[PDB]
Amino acid sequence: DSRVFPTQRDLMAGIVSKHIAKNMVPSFIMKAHESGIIHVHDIDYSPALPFTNCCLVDLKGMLENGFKLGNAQIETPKSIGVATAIMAQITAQVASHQYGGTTFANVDKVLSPYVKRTYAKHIEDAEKWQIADALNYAQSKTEKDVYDAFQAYEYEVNTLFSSNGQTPFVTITFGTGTDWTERMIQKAILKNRIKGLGRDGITPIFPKLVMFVEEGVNLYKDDPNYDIKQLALECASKRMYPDIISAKNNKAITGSSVPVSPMGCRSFLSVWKDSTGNEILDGRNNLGVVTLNLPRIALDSYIGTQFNEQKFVELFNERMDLCFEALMCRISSLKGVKATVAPILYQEGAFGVRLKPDDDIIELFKNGRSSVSLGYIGIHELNILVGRDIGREILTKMNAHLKQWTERTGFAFSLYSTPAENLCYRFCKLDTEKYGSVKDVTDKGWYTNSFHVSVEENITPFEKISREAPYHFIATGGHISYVELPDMKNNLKGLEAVWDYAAQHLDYFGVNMPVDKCMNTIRRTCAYLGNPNE
Amino acid sequence: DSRVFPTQRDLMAGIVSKHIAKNMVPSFIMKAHESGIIHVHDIDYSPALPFTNCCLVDLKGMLENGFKLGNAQIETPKSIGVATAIMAQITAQVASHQYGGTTFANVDKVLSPYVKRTYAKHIEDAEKWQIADALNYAQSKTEKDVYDAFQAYEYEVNTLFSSNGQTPFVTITFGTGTDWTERMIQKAILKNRIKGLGRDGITPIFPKLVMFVEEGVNLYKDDPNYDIKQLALECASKRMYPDIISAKNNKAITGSSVPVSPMGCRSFLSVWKDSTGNEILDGRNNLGVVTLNLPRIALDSYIGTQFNEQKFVELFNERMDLCFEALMCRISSLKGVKATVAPILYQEGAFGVRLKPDDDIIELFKNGRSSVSLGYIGIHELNILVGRDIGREILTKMNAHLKQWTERTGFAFSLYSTPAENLCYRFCKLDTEKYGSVKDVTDKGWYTNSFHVSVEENITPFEKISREAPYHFIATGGHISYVELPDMKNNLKGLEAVWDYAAQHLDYFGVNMPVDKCMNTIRRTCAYLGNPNE
């Protein structure tokens, strides 16, 4: 809410920070942001404080070894219920030290050792109490211990607030686990999600659930986990989540030999290797987002009422540079900042390393370890303004710019399809104060997300999936495609159809359907789940 | 820490609030605070925001009925481990909506129904698996379920941060429970506390542990829970806590027919009844503290180098009024504030009622339900400055003023022995900028806490306890006495001696001893536990 204390204290800190940013960001960058030319995200956090954006938490390396959480020296969990309890405490802590989402990748694989542990204890207890049905007593207890554990993770995520009086934006991914412990975790999460939250079993907005689907594991009636896929479909039909990621396309796009979980909503890392040649994923992050307002480059290049191509070219080049200056300006503020700024992130392992209190954090992000995002929005409205479809082309040229940035600074710049849950209105409003109502651009009040096909089009699901799929291979830093569907609670084979089509053709995908009960109304009209009643 | 993000964001909010307070507090009150005449506590929170101070959480009325925690509608816990998990989530939430400590009173009595529940499940499971040793299988599981549950409460308290990037100031009290479930909870807490936190089993600073000791329950070798008292002694000897409260004296002082737990460190409520004649304790709170600098009234009444009695009288009367104006000024800012400001406190039961989002919260605090604190400090240094012991007398007159305030406004003003962990240095420093080094007053650098006997005196434990005990009956709004003792890990009968003496003579009491391990050094030099190494 906003009338609430934690939110109010946060707004105060936001205000002080926006003011401090005015004294740190070169005026030409602030003026372009104030006017809607670009959008420097999270200015109410950074650069006042050297926060970073989103991340894949290295939960595996923290549970295995131990780590200091506050005053306490936590030790490897002896139980699955203790490892998820700890996962929640880490979720709360990481949320409070970065301003972006937090992702726990492959919880099925990561937490499996603890499910095994729980089992060993129910067996050493099935003989300690000479229990009739031994192997069966374990199977049950363990199963219950695992459901309750994720049910409690899910509950904790929904009650625990950050340092901002907000519920954490956390993402949990699974799907590539085949072992019985890995399968049990997956089912546990899907089952508990269907059950819903609390007495009225309502639909949770967090954690976001993303499932990997790969041939020979998940998508064909013959794979080991095809039954989980079925459960996942039901879940999606009743709670919107999980979204799915195509292991096949995801690996080709990222260059990673293992599926890449999105940090936060949809920010994807590119493949990276440590000094000894190892492919690292967990513990990596993103340094921020600066979004480029694409319709506005077209609008500003109109002469009278017609488009001027030569003007577009000059402005596009001018604005790409501006964006670059904006991303570097804040990355530069990270210089000289010490690991003392966020112990959970830099010292106790969430970022997969152990820096001393006096080590500079900036060194950890260099040479491609961290990604940096150049966002964009409204290809649909840009196409309309320039007379034709330049979607794939503008993005391709943006990437060529990004490659040069990467080679000059060492940071791994990528193209990001900004979720823009609110930026979609903000850019449109600022452009409207200058151009008024422009048919099919600023007239509906918002811009279309990244490269998505406008909502006003009457596209068949497969067409939409097909018209959007190539963007998943161009905007490698972050992307997703949605399809609108009616209630499919009783048409799972239909939803599986859409899933299988998206899975083959694109990367990250999700389905928007209506999900209401005797009054708990949820819709995903943009990026997050929400009640469009308020 | 301070270099840490959550702390930094908080400092920003603190700054904005101190500035806002400058525009809300009458200048004469700010000037008296800036000069050390009085100390308006928590100005970095209130009155910028209508926060309240400390409280006794009505956990009983929240677990019994249900309540909304965020989005979720939590239901009565079916297990003890689920009720303590929930207790932690409530602890985190309440901490974020008030700026003072939070107390869970008589957790032994309150949580007992859930321990029973856990038992019923291990029995209905001892037959479901035709377990040999039935009643014995329950006894064990239940016992383990209960240890682990409080161990996890204790851990969560130490990892969970508030909206301020701080660990919550929470107090847990027990001791009057006799039932086997009540005893089990107590032992669980004492046992887990001795065990310590984390791998190195270090000493927790929170939760504070306070135990009631009453004849025919706790203190004589013949009472049911005398063995818990023994355990408590061991605990105190190894972890400083628990402190104890004399049920006998506590009830006579508070006027309550049941022992009164301190909200936060040592703030005690006076007896109060609802509209139907019921004695309410749980869900009640305190509206703030304004501390009066006693040495400074004496100092300002010196003429040249000698005390001037007539001047003292005039200043004391002038400053009491000033204090009153300071307490009312902030209570007045609570007018018109809606329950939407803190749902967990006002709507979902932590304050024992259910206000609608649009109800004013101020009505809930009136006619004695909430206490309001007039603090004071340094009787020792005041006695030195006025030539004789006026301790008991000045306090008695303060109370006569408080009674008049209570009758004119309806709020229940009480005399509070400010913990002043830092105020003790601040008042001394501000008085030193004006008077320099004054032998036995401002020369050591700090003032002595409330009515405590100076540390520089060489008093026997019983003497100290005896010289201080009468203050517990005068400063009813908050008080405590400490005794310094050597290592008593191997002299428990000695510590029990001190305990029994304090128990008979005063109210709330604690013992400071050294508590170190292969380097985890803890001391309570003032109010809280801490490492005097930094």
Image (cartoon, coloured by chain):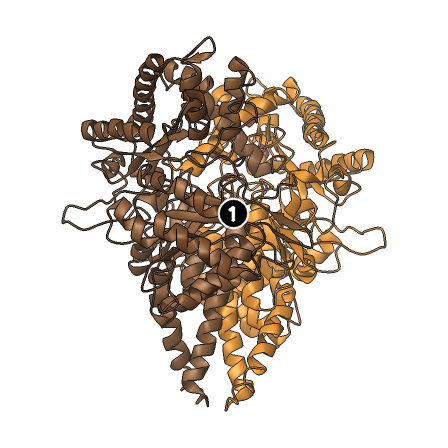
Chain colours: A orange, B brown
Q: Mark 1: which amino acid? A: Pro
Q: Quadrant of residue A415?
A: top right
Residue found farthest to the top: B304
Q: Quadrant of the C terminus of chain A?
A: top left
Q: Position of residue A349 (x, y in %)?
A: 69, 51
Badge 1: residue crowd in 10 Å (few <14, some 14–19, many ≥20): many
B212 lies above or below B365: below
Depth order, front residue of A86/A210:
A86
Q: Is residue A430 above or below residue A199?
A: above
Q: Residue at x 51, y 41 (%)?
A: A163
Q: Which of the two residues, B417 or B55, is positioned nearer the viewer here? A: B417
- Which one is nearer the viewer's eye here, A94 or A409? A94
Q: Chain of mark 1?
A: A
Residue B282 in sight from this viewpoint: no
Please give the count of numbered marks on the rendered protein: 1
Q: Nearer the viewer, residue B528 or B117?
A: B528
- Residue A520: which quarter of the image? bottom left
Residue B415 seen by the camera = yes
Q: Measured from the top left, where is residue B137 in percent x and y?
A: 45, 82
Task: Classify the position of the N terminus of chain A by image quarter.
Answer: top left
Which residue is farthest right? A276
B283 with respect to B166 (left or right) = left
Q: Residue at x 28, y 58 (%)?
A: B65
Query: In the image, is residue A186 above or below residue B198?
Result: below
Residue found at the very far left of the displayed protein: B276
Q: Residue at x 43, y 65 (%)?
A: B228
Could you say which quadrant of the image residue A200 lies in?
bottom left
Relative image position of residue A466 (x, y in whole percent): 60, 53
Instruction: Find disc 1 in the rendering and name its residue.
Output: A168
Residue A45 percent coordinates (x, y): 57, 33
Where disc 1 sits, the SS reads loop
